[PDB]
Image (tube, helix red, strand yellow):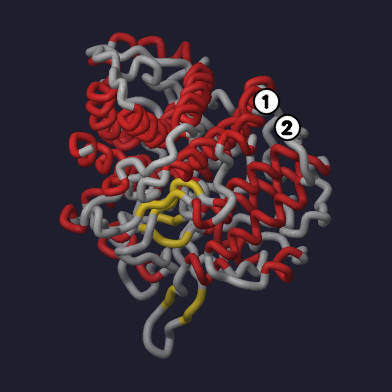
């Protein structure tokens, strides 16, 4: 499959921006746009040591240039190589070529799931029609269509027992059975994503996703989908540019609050201890940077340059889907009677698997903990004036321990989503999507109080943008985009809620 190789590897590096060490900071600038200074910053996985003069998405200013950039990083960059593969394989009678196309379809769909979850409507079904003016699908149609497409991929790949494109497969070394598991896992994630808005659709596929005869889902760490440097394609983890080169990405307040309050051993696995001051004055510890930082970049010994940093090296991988997520998805599914089983069991196994994924121990002690997330007081925060008590009306790790502010079922979901949030790190887009859909976990409020106003929201209804908006000028190049607001059911702005946002979405008490 020489004709598919380069194109397929390009696709894989595009799902979540990453590239060859020779491209230096390029892929890293892209990851900033998709994960680090945007989504990951909004939900508190990271904190920015910069405000970019309030000129970009970090502070919710969705400019034409940055949104066009986002469209490229979430949709168009991967469209290119996929389209060529499609053109070459779409009419092949060769089963091995059909398999290649379906594997390419899975990779495309994992990437475009992010695209629709970020923008809402996208050109999904029209993809490949060679149109100069792509027609967009409503988000509901994108979801319905993707589920059908995933089942199609699984049906075909389930008949393939030999290796496919091993030399160019940076994820599973040509093991089609694992690709099937990834496809069904994505199907599971999608079904859970729609159960609140469309339970019927959820039920139409969740059973097929978990049905053993269809290949199974990712339940073992050995089946996780991740990409990292290898002989097939050397790579430089794309978080390095922003973390070490630009000194802009640091540990977020929200995730720190949970890790600290829950006495989570993953705190040390995910982040480094920062330093404040120098010499005998230097204080060491886990110092977070608030979400949507309103302060300018600084590099003194008392600055965020030395706040806790994400632990990562050039050979570190980026994760597409991990076994722990599967368990949390099953937990929620069982909680709402979509599948059989005990929510608590799936919940605790998800945490156990996450600890194993991170190489940490003490899961039993962690599971019996009844502590609440730690708030950030004006005193504790050292990079400006900021405070938010994350503990208020929040929940603990222990399944049977209820705060009682929300209904019991609602708090159980809160525990599931909060723990999934912790296990998903650093998959920011998925965490951001899950927060917007459920309202969990509760987040540290943005520091820049002017940010919500930039997307048409207020400091009470939005702690994060509800979506990215398309670049206004893009409408000039494609007349089919004029329909976007109607497809959205609202204005093309960051405050417009996407299709899967559940009704009666909870908010942290005041």
User: Can you tell which quarter of the image residue 247 is in?
Assistant: bottom left
Taking depth in this image into account, of 258 and 422 the one nearest to the observer is 422
Residue reaching furthest to the left: 22
Could you tell me residue 193's position as x and y percent?
A: 59, 32
Q: Which residue is mark 1?
A: 203
Cβ–Cβ below 8 Å for labels 2 and 1? yes
Could you tell me residue 2's position as x and y percent?
A: 19, 39
Q: Does 336 sit left or right of 173 as displayed?
A: right
> Would you place residue 87 above or below residue 117 in this image?
above
Q: Does 420 sit left or right of 334 as displayed?
A: left
Q: Residues within 10 Å of mark 1 (few under 14, many from 20)?
A: some
Could you tell me residue 282's position as x and y percent?
A: 43, 83
Q: Which residue is mark 2?
A: 338
**Mark 1 element type:** helix
Could you tell me residue 32's position as x and y percent?
A: 33, 48
Please give the count of numbered marks on the rendered protein.
2
> Would you place residue 87 above or below residue 338 in this image?
above
Taking depth in this image into account, of 101 and 33 the one nearest to the observer is 101
Image point (73%, 71%), residue name:
365
User: Can you tell which quarter of the image residue 132 is in?
Assistant: top left
Quote the CA–CA distance across marks 2 and 1: 7 Å
């Amino acid at each position: 499959p020489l004709k598919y190789g380069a194109r397929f590897m390009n696709m894989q590096q595009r799902v979540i921006p990453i590239g060859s060490p020779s491209l230096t900071t390029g892929p890293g600038n892209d990851l900033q746009n998709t994960d680090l200074i945007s989504s990951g910053n909004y939900i508190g996985y990271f904190g920015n040591n910069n405000n970019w003069g309030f000129n970009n998405e970090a502070n919710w200013n969705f400019t034409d240039s940055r949104m066009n950039y986002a469209y490229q990083n979430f949709y168009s960059q991967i469209f290119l190589p996929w389209n060529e593969i499609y053109e070459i394989a779409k009419d092949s009678d060769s089963p091995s070529e059909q398999a290649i196309l379906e594997i390419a379809n899975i990779v495309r769909n994992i990437a475009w799931l992010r695209a629709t979850d970020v923008f809402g409507p996208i050109a999904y079904n029209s993809a490949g029609d060679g149109s100069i003016a792509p027609k967009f699908d409503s988000q509901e149609v994108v979801y319905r269509s993707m589920l059908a497409d995933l089942s199609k991929s699984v049906e075909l790949l389930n008949t393939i027992s030999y290796s496919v494109m091993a030399q160019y497969d940076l994820i599973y070394n040509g093991n089609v059975q694992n690709w099937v598991k990834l496809a069904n896992s994505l199907m599971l994630r999608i079904v859970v994503r729609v159960h609140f808005i469309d339970e019927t659709l959820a039920k139409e596929y969740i059973t097929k996703a978990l049905d053993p005869k269809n290949g199974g889902v990712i339940e073992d760490i050995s089946s996780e989908a991740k990409i990292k440097s290898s002989d097939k394609m050397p790579l430089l983890n794309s978080m390095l540019a922003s973390v070490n080169e630009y000194n802009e990405t640091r540990m977020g307040a929200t995730i720190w609050g949970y890790l600290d309050g829950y006495k989570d051993p993953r705190l040390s696995a995910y982040f480094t201890e920062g330093t404040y001051g120098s010499g005998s004055w230097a204080q060491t510890g886990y110092f977070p940077v608030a979400p949507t930082n309103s302060k300018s970049k600084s590099e003194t010994s008392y600055s965020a340059k030395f706040a806790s940093r994400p632990k990562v090296d050039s050979n570190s991988p980026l994760y597409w889907f991990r076994a722990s997520e599967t368990y949390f998805l099953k937990a929620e599914a069982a909680l709402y009677n979509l599948i059989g089983g005990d929510p608590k069991t799936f919940y605790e196994q998800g945490i156990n698997i996450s600890f194993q994924e991170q190489g940490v121990s003490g899961v039993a002690t962690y599971l019996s903990g009844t502590g609440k997330p730690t708030g950030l007081t004006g005193s504790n925060y050292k990079y400006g004036t900021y405070n938010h008590d994350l503990s208020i009306g929040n929940t603990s790790p222990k399944w049977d321990d209820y705060t009682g502010n929300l209904s019991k079922q609602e708090e159980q979901l809160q525990k599931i989503i909060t723990q999934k949030y912790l296990a998903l790190y650093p998959n920011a887009v998925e965490a951001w999507t899950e927060y917007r859909r459920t309202g969990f976990p509760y987040l540290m409020k943005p520091m820049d109080e002017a940010a919500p106003g930039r997307i048409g929201a207020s400091i009470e209804d939005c702690r994060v943008p509800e979506r990215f908006r398309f670049a206004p000028t893009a409408y000039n190049s494609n007349p089919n985009m004029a329909e976007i607001p109607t497809l959205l059911g609202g204005g093309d702005i960051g405050a417009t809620k996407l299709w899967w946002v559940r009704s009666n979405r909870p908010k942290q008490p005041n």
